[PDB]
Amino acid sequence: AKNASEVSELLAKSLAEKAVVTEGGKVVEGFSYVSKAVAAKVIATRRAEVHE
Amino acid sequence: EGNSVAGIIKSVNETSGANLLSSLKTIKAQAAPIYPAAASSTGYSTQAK
């Protein structure tokens, strides 16, 4: 019971990270998107290796 | 005995970005020219005698 908030956060994050995309209610299966955190991570590692 | 600059270029290339600046003095000293040590005397060799 004292980690009942923690298991809810874990279930919410598990549903959140495997999120699907809909355009008008129905899902576009086989859709690939790259987030701005992923793109900024790629930019950060590329800037780090050119700087070194 | 290869030349010192290929050793400098190699030892800088195969060094990561975190251990770069700490490991510059060992690359400075590994490509320094040899100045041989002042050994013992045992002076007045056979031509001097």
Image (tube, coloured by chain):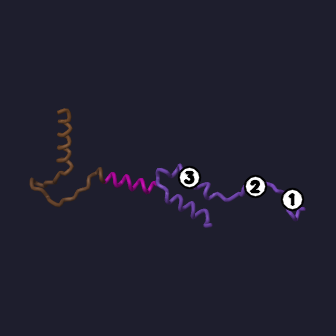
Chain colours: A brown, B purple
| Mark 3 lies on residue | B24
Count of number-bearing discs: 3
Q: Secondary structure at mark 3?
A: helix
> Tag 2: residue type?
Ala
Q: Chain of mark 2?
A: B
Q: Secondary structure at mark 1?
A: loop
Badge 3 crowding class, 10 Å Cα cut-off, few under 14, some 14 to 19, many 20 or more, is some
Q: On residue B39, which mark appears?
A: 2
* Residue at (71, 57) in percent of width and height: B35
| Mark 1 lies on residue | B44
Asked if residue A41 is among those painted magenta in the image, a careful observer would answer yes
Cα–Cα gap, marks 1 and 3: 43 Å
Foreground tag (1 vs 3): 1
Q: Are marks 1 and 3 on the same chain?
A: yes
Badge 1 crowding class, 10 Å Cα cut-off, few under 14, some 14 to 19, many 20 or more, is few
Find residue A11 and report its horizontal and vertical position in percent.
17, 44
Report the side of B28 relative to B40 (left or right). Answer: left
Region in magenta? A39-52
Find residue A17 and report its horizontal and vertical position in percent.
21, 49
Q: Is there a contact, CB below 8 Å, between mark 1 and mark 3?
A: no
> Tag 1: residue type?
Tyr
